[PDB]
Image (cartoon, rainbow over all chains, first blue to last red; front, side, top):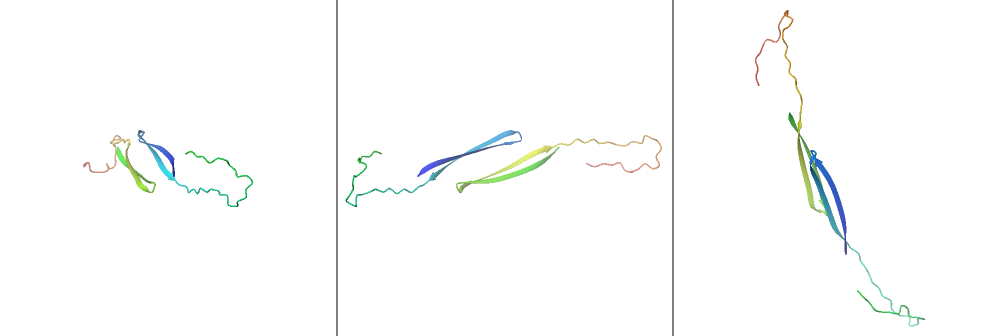
Length: 58
Length: 58
């Protein structure tokens, strides 16, 4: 989930005095499904393994 | 001077909850000049005078 933001403004004047300005700011939530996969040597005959490191950081 | 009246309304909904309705009612003043005249026998020879009453009410 992440959030995004709209910002809408309009201005209105009445009898040349009394200026009204409203500023609306809507915050909505955008969702997304992810599916993480991972490869395993299941054919038992590789030439070279590939991608020689396995350390992580968050 | 007399007064006249406008009435404006619009409705707005945000995120399907929180319905906003504003109802504005403007009262303005309309002006007018009047000039009241009155006729006088200045030729001294009428046949008949005309309009035989002179009483008023407000």
